[PDB]
Amino acid sequence: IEFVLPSPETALLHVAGHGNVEQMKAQVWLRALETSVAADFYHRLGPHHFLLLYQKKGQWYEIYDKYQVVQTLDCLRYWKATHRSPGQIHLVQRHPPSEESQAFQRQLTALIGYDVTDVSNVHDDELEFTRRGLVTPRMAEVASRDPKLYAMHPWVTSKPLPEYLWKKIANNCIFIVIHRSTTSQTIKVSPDDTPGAILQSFFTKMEQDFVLRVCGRDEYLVGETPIKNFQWVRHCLKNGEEIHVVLDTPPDPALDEVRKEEWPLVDDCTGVTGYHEQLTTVSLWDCDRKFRVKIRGIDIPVLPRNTDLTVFVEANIQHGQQVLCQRRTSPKPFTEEVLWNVWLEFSIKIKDLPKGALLNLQIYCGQLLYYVNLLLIDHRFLLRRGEYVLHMWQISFNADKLTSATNPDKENSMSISILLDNYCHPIALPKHQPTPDPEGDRVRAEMPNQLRKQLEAIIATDPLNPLTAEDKELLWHFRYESLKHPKAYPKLFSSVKWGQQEIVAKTYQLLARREVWDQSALDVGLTMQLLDCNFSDENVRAIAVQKLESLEDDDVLHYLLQLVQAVKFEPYHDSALARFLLKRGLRNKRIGHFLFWFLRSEIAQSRHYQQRFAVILEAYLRGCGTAMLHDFTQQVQVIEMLQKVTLDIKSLSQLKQKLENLQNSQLPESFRVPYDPGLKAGALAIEKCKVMASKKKPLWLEFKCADPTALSNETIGIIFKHGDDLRQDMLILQILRIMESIWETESLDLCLLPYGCISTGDKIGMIEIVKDATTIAKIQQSTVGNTGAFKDEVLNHWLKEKSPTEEKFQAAVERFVYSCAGYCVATFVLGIGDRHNDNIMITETGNLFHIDFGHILGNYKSFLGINKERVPFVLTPDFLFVMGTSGKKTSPHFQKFQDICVKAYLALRHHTNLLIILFSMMLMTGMPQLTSKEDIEYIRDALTVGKNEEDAKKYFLDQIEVCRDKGWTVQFNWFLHLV
Amino acid sequence: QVQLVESGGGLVQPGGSLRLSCAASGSIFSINAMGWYRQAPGKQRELVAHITSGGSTNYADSVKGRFTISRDNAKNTVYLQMNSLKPEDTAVYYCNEAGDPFLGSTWNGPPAFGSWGQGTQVTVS
């Protein structure tokens, strides 16, 4: 193999096989030193190590591996494919990064809030290798990037227009107002016309390099799509407002420039692992010995006083929340340092260990106190060996219990010392599957009719339905028949015995011939099921991601937070879901913005997955252009300074002085709103800001709009609060939006509107202010409710006062009925229906809201209200009096409310499966505490799984009746508890 | 293998009506949403009518108010009822397993199925 030394010297080496030939660094070093006195001189001045580069596709690649030459099989395969026997490898000096690179890295660190280059809490190079490996998708997305559409990021959907919106088009025409300087002209256009056609019509109705931008917002109506397919156009149609656009010059694509990538490409880590024949290094499948681990001891500087006098260690081998084997140590007195030095031998073979298996070490007292996880197979298909001293996590099913990260608090957490068996040669797990040539003896005989019926019934069941041993055996024995039905994939793969190598090989053969799945229609619930905690195998995840790859940008935006949370379920840092999220955030600007904020919140608040999300955020930030970087920097600056001011105020006219200090110093002239990238906030209306009379003391801030083209002088309401976790609020609001879309596809407009919520840091966040909205508790306290006495006419009189005319009042009543029904159904399904008046808001137009979901979500998870009087949802006598005449018999408005809520309940029951998987993900990810069964099953009990539509309708009517039974009792109890 | 056979098409005058039927050979028909696709001459195939396993119906904008889709899980057959036919409705109509109604990717373009049947020809003239 030809080598180029750094003096363009060409030294001809030879192919030295693949057995421990990574000493080629030393071999070439010695060859250069002997063949050149200059190399001998530079040996005293050169860096510690050098690099290997070659030409894959014109771009420089790097051999980033110091273990074996079998990893370098990719460059050899490329060289043979190109038919170039003498291969060229260049050595490059390990140049330190330049000052500009260091400054860019510091800027990225400031944006992320976590130091990705720190290696003080890692025992391997998985995160660094993930950083090196995320370059190729980033460069692929940057290369295949259309500059104009990326700069302008049109927001379009391909769904048909809703019936209530399709009817709203008066005469199959849409009025658009185009503003040019001070001139305003209204043009009538058909809903099936592209914006280019509208622009051409406007120009003919008197240069051509112009576009339509929404007045007062950073949204462009461009691209080749009908005007009715724009999300802002649909938003304006739904609200009945006029569509105002301005003729603006297109934004410069040069502002989205991305600086050149500084690292060479890293290839893949699958080179080290080959087929079973190639690896029989030592093949993992050759070792038939049982797995064994030594628990050396337990160390803790300060003993907790929670529980003592007895302690032991439990070692579990699990693959996707299924414990393959379980071993325990002899209990010992609970003191500062406990010593065992005992080998725990499991009944599972070493060859049968599946990739993604987790060694779960837990400390029990006498109940579970500390836990820590260790991935048995590392990212490079190698079994873990040697000493490991892991700092454990302290508990205060959960996604936090699956993390392979170590506790960063080295000086205060409990530490466990373990030992794993060592070997002379590294043990490498062979490749997943060479080829499905034998077909694994696919079944030929047709299933008996009764067995076919049993299999169909098993497939038709809900995701939460447990599978018996007979059910699993039937699913596996007829796997090739179950492939024809994509709905059976989660159940088919739940019946796989992952603790046997041969069964895993059969499963890999089975999924190597997936065609019915490939052409199958994209089902969101099924794919999210395949990404849950119950699937730790990489190939099932890849299948789910490749199905997700056919989504559109709006569809991804609907489920972006859920996928970000599901990244936690990935056993390894460099997963297909991470690549998919990075690619879709680099493709679209809105997706990138929301992904940045969602990921930064998790970095700030979740220590278990800080490093992985930090690496993903680094990849995205390097991918995006400099305009996005500047906007992110401005947003982070304003967020940090508002956080500091919130801290100072919470420590205690002072707010006015501090806001004046901010406005004249370091406050950016304009910043993008984190929960609405299309809106830019400018100066701060200090004379309107205040501090609300709440226990958390949030900041009521109002910013002026930074766009001069805005049609209104209305400010931008922003609430900054500290001491509450807004992540649960974001999850609840996202699920509300998903249910709103589900109702939309069934011609149901429940008037349920979620507000803007973004968590910006540790227990801080930003809340959108809904204008002209007040709280039901305040409405009561205006007349009666300060002392606890309650009246029914207060809400009706308040709505009557805010309505100038009778038609406005009737519209307000209709909106109140629809919003109340929608929120009742949504909160009953989600289990957050038992709230107090202080967390329910209402506008002057009648719309109803539920706020502060984090306050009630944790309380309901901890208590479930089984020890109190729980109501399914807030159907308060004031609501009934607003709806009907409160005659306790019926009313046309009450009948309409009952009908629409039953319709919404049946609509949600139509997508029970997706709702169930969303609820499960929400519980296991968004809950700081530990959940289990009987809590996940709440949704399948509330969604009335396995019952008729009439039975479900009767059940929901019974829930309404029991709400009507307890009129003021629950509200009075809440008042007494709070007071 | 899932097999679908479409029937009911033919020549009809403008303003007329037609009723298509299609029988599916998939025995899990009960839990699968189905939809009707049409391929205009020199045009890509597009979903026009969507029905869920429960029975909720969603239609494309062009065919809204004139097309009605129904299913019978007992006979594993899906019916599409056309009213007030217009010349642009002339296309080859197909039925298959549709997708998610609220997903925009389903309404986007060809759903990349590999089990398309023969279809039926509808001509309005």
Image: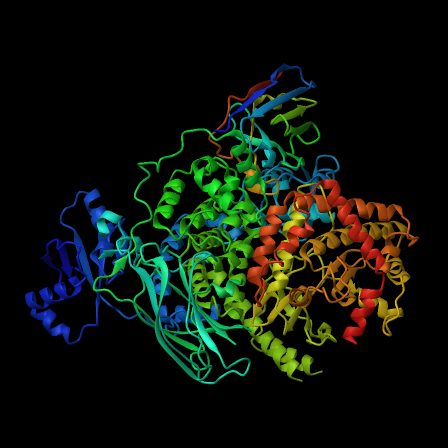
Foreground of the two, A807 or B83: B83
Image mark count: 0
* In the displayed structure image, the side of residue A243 where residue A842 appears, left or right: right
* In the displayed structure image, the side of residue A699 where residue A497 appears, left or right: left
Residue A130 position, x and y percent, is: 37, 60
Quarter of the C terminus of chain A within the rendering: bottom right
> Is residue A92 depicted above or below A647 in this figure?
above
Foreground of the two, A716 or A422: A422
Q: Residue furthest front?
A: A330
Foreground of the two, A330 or A832: A330
* In the displayed structure image, the side of residue A835 where residue B62 appears, left or right: left
Which residue shows up at 26% across the image and 49% down it? Answer: A276
Residue A478 shows in the view = yes
Residue A267 shows in the view = no
Which residue shows up at 61% across the image and 63% down it? Answer: A728
Colouring chosen for the image of the structure: rainbow
Residue B69 position, x and y percent, is: 66, 29
The quadrant where residue A324 appears: bottom left
* In the displayed structure image, the side of residue B83 where residue B90 appears, left or right: left
Residue A524 position, x and y percent, is: 55, 46
> Is residue B116 depicted above or below A887 in this figure?
above
Residue A844 position, x and y percent, is: 81, 59
